[PDB]
Image (spheres, coloured by chain):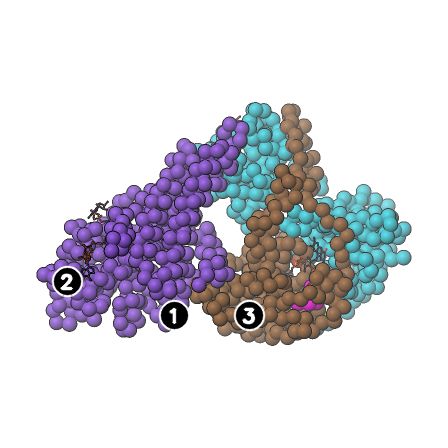
Chain colours: A cyan, B purple, C brown
Amino acid sequence: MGNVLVVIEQRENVIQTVSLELLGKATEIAKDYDTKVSALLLGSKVEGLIDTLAHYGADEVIVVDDEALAVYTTEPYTKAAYEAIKAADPIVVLFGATSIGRDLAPRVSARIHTGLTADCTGLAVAEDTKLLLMTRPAFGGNIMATIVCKDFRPQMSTVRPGVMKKNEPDETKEAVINRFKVEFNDADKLVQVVQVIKEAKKQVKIEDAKILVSAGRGMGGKENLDILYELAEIIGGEVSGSRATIDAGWLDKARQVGQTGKTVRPDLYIACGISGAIQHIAGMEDAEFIVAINKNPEAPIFKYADVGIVGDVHKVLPELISQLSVAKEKG
Amino acid sequence: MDLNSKKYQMLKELYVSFAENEVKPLATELDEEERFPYETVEKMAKAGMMGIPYPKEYGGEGGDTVGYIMAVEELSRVCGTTGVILSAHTSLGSWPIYQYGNEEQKQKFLRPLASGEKLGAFGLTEPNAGTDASGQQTTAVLDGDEYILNGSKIFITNAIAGDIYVVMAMTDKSKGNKGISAFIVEKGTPGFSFGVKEKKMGIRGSATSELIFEDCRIPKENLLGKEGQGFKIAMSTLDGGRIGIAAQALGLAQGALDETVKYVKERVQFGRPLSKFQNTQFQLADMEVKVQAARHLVYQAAINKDLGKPYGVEAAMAKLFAAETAMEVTTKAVQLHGGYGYTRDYPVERMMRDAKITEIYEGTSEVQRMVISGKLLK
Amino acid sequence: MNIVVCIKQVPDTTEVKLDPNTGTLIRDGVPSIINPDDKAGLEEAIKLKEEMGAHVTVITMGPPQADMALKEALAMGADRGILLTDRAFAGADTWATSSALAGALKNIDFDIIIAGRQAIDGDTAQVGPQIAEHLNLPSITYAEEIKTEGEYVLVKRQFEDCCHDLKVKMPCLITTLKDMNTPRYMKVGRIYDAFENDVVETWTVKDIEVDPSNLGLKGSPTSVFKSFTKSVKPAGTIYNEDAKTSAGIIIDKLKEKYII
Ligand SMILES: Cc1cc2nc3c(=O)[nH]c(=O)nc-3n(C[C@H](O)[C@H](O)[C@H](O)COP(=O)(O)OP(=O)(O)OC[C@H]3O[C@@H](n4cnc5c(N)ncnc54)[C@H](O)[C@@H]3O)c2cc1C
Ligand SMILES: Cc1cc2nc3c(=O)[nH]c(=O)nc-3n(C[C@H](O)[C@H](O)[C@H](O)COP(=O)(O)OP(=O)(O)OC[C@H]3O[C@@H](n4cnc5c(N)ncnc54)[C@H](O)[C@@H]3O)c2cc1C
Ligand SMILES: Cc1cc2nc3c(=O)[nH]c(=O)nc-3n(C[C@H](O)[C@H](O)[C@H](O)COP(=O)(O)OP(=O)(O)OC[C@H]3O[C@@H](n4cnc5c(N)ncnc54)[C@H](O)[C@@H]3O)c2cc1C
Ligand SMILES: CC(C)(COP(=O)(O)OP(=O)(O)OC[C@H]1O[C@@H](n2cnc3c(N)ncnc32)[C@H](O)[C@@H]1OP(=O)(O)O)[C@@H](O)C(=O)NCCC(=O)NCCSS
Ligand SMILES: [Ca+2]
Ligand SMILES: [Ca+2]
């Protein structure tokens, strides 16, 4: 047979979590094929990341240590993975659908002349035909299609981070280390990295924001919004609010949501202490997922919430912060 | 020829994106601060507008008046003051120089305008001479190789901001309106001074103010047309501008209608949205018919001008009927928003205040009636 | 200096909603537009036309309607337009698409090729680098700024955490990002003449250099097995306890995928 290969991503010598999730789905696909699971590790001084991979389900760890892989630049990575994948002959190759993954994979699958499915959210091999059914969301997300690579091998896909579930780390299992040598010459080093500068996360407008934590009259004061901005930090979204809060001097008009503020259609909306008049609801009714906290279970906002929590803002919010801050402390 | 051509479609696509992104989110800041939109003038110029229907050889874009009127319509749809800044610039200031100015003149004055590098204005109305236009009191007398100008023009759109002024004055009072001449006057000349920008009901962004001429010395080379032609020059200029304003009304009417349709669906009272009550529908119906009716009258005037058929009566029917239609529709619009319509957080009220002036300036609806009935009775 | 931009006319999938009272997605009303990453690229090219004196050519693969995309692009400042239409491409996946476009580029003088990161209707973000691979050109993605010095391009590459300042000797392919710039409006008169005179070239397969067994479905490795519409959102639950409450919040969040 072939093998199920996951292409690992590392950033300044730390494995990205989506890799370990992908080894998760990898052991399932491989078990459905009666083959084992392989890891492609790429980097400069990437020694020791290897034992980690072994623990998270990898059976073979293909290693390419070179100072040409020190920093990510498309071609050295493409050439390397091509050589290594072509050499292992996998039935299936998975990359994490990141800015590296979605740059590297399309170039690799072209050089191989196979097929590639992008930003996937679901994978499983059919009972009949034993093809990998790779399901991805398209058309701005309003469509869910399932694509197969009928004839060409390896079946390739970039997979969405956060969707596949990891394996239980096993400290006993070591894996086989493959120690794959690759030469890198001029016609590959064509892109030159002048500077690697890391800047901050770049504040965005609420109309464009991905998550909104939204202040209502319920909060009861300007400094009481700090607890929101605190939570806004832990999820990345910005804080918006009802005309109530803006009027009262707590936020810029630029954060007002509704018929005479801004109309916002983000992936998450948390209404903290908002009653929800139509003046406000017709501003955000079209969000993908709305969560609301209020003391009044007869608040009309609950009439719109996918999750209506009935409670005190100043007692739910800090409990939501403590539960999440231990969430990304541990994982 | 035909007006559903993809050419015009592509213009409309441009206008709409400029309107929503550059003009719409300034609208009420200009209403409340009662401020001229210098920014969206320079932005406007850059994307081609400000010279839409003038030959390229003079710095305009090579378009037709239909694509220009389309622009006034799509601007007033979102912000009425901005609509007039344009329509006044292209129709009232630029065009008389295009039509009646010689080659030297079309190069020194018409090009800065058509390229958006400068801003144009037309000054005809005086305190004692409004609808009776021939009772001009500002004088021009020729002295050497200069004209001297003395008097006042009130209510002039795009005063202070404007750079070139096409003003009218008597050069021979003892001939009535066969005694008015027209002059091109550059802002900066000694003696040319401004009023105080007026306080008005709705078009509050548009800078309207007084022109003051105290022994104002002008080059004789600035006489637009012949001596004594000015009356006919101003009369035919207004025929064009009436089209611009009719479309301004149209813009307003269509924007106010667009807003109510949005609202009447979101707002629920009595278990069902407002859009579900037979009266709100029937009112919306009557409004859309008046707007459509008006559309046809406006553009048939434009079409006429571009084909060089006569267009002055056509323009007057468009001015009368769109002005009325703007007023009825904006009013029904606020009504249909209910209490919220009357607040200034929503734009419908501003549209209603904007609308009212479209019955007055560039000739009052009564003047239009005089025109239409005159070509009918012989 | 020759710049070729690949724009794709797409239906604006932000403006797509699914009618709860029918179930399917709202069919009409969605305007067709230059996909925005593409408009962005087109912006960066015309910027270069204005600074360096470059020559912007624009090409789109699609049906006659995609003419309008090129006309929009032309009135924005482009110089040339190519509309590439053929029955052959029916069913093309991203391999059979990048190769089609690549084969055209064999006949379009270039020094920089610009495409968008992602087309908002297929959503793969795969054609740009596959084109660059077919033509065996260095490629740069997730581009946030583009400058040139002499024979070299300088590009900022945007990442999750860092961003690289890069340098390439022309030729090269660059995929550009929806933000990074704000795209200039058309000029009237540019619209008037782009329609009044009309220099827009329409190429068929005859005009490209490709193995025809690399076109269309028959040339496409991947293929669509099943495809089904988005499920309509469900009822929504309303809850009464505390601190079990935040767990209420976080376990439904874990369900819609933000396990971090
Ligand atoms: C012309 C006009 C335009 C308007 N435009 C807008 C607009 O664009 N956007 C907008 O938002 N509004 C707008 N409004 C106002 C809108 O109708 C409401 O006034 C608005 O919803 C008030 O904000 P709110 O829900 O936060 O406040 P309230 O409705 O006063 O609700 C506060 C809620 O907090 C709850 N509560 C209080 N303390 C707590 C606590 N400790 N824990 C839990 N729950 C608590 C209460 O039960 C109540 O439900 C407009 C009004 C007018 C007249
Ligand atoms: C905001 C604003 C901007 C303006 N901008 C300009 C500009 O840029 N350039 C410019 O030249 N002018 C401009 N004007 C002047 C405007 O065009 C005049 O107000 C208009 O021509 C009417 O003249 P009037 O104000 O003196 O009205 P009047 O002539 O005093 O008339 C008032 C009323 O009497 C009626 N009436 C008058 N005579 C008769 C009659 N014979 N028969 C029946 N009814 C009659 C009118 O129809 C009207 O209802 C502007 C005015 C305003 C308000
Ligand atoms: C529901 C669905 C799912 C699909 N899934 C896959 C899949 O998993 N794998 C796969 O290989 N194909 C897939 N396809 C096929 C793919 O959408 C088409 O081949 C399309 O031609 C390329 O994908 P894209 O539209 O995602 O473009 P992208 O790869 O997002 O676009 C990249 C860039 O290429 C340029 N470009 C793209 N198309 C054109 C064009 N027609 N003309 C000019 N320039 C262009 C633009 O600059 C664009 O920004 C799918 C199609 C559908 C309808
Ligand atoms: C123009 C003005 C000042 C008054 O003058 P005016 O309208 O030109 O009137 P006249 O030319 O003297 O009358 C024409 C006569 O010629 C007659 N006539 C035409 N042909 C003829 C012929 N072959 N043989 C004999 N008589 C003839 C007509 O019968 C008519 O007589 P009636 O009065 O019985 O109808 C005024 O009426 C006006 O319309 N002002 C408009 C201003 C405006 O729009 N201002 C807004 C600017 S603000 S931005
Ligand atoms: Ca190589
Ligand atoms: Ca200000």
The residue singled out by tag 2 in the image is B179
| Amino acid type of the residue that numbered disc 3 sits on in the rendered structure | Val
The residue depicted at 28 percent of the width and 73 percent of the height is B103
Which region is colored magenta?
Answer: C97-101
Nearer the observer: mark 1 or 2; the answer is: 2
Residue C98, magenta (yes or no): yes
Residue A107 in view in this figure: no
Local crowd size for mark 3, using a 10 Å CA cut-off: few (<14), some (14–19), many (≥20): some
Mark 3 → mark 1, Cα distance in angstroms = 22 Å
Residue C67: percent from left, percent from top? 57, 64
Which residue is under mark 1?
B56
Q: Secondary structure at mark 3?
A: loop
Q: In terms of secondary structure, where does tag 1 sit?
A: helix
Which residue does the numbered mark 3 point to in the structure image?
Answer: C200
Question: Residue B41 vs residue B153: left or right?
Answer: right
Q: Secondary structure at mark 2?
A: helix
Chain that bears disc 1: B
- Residue B183 placement: quadrant: bottom left
Q: Are marks 3 and 1 on the same chain?
A: no
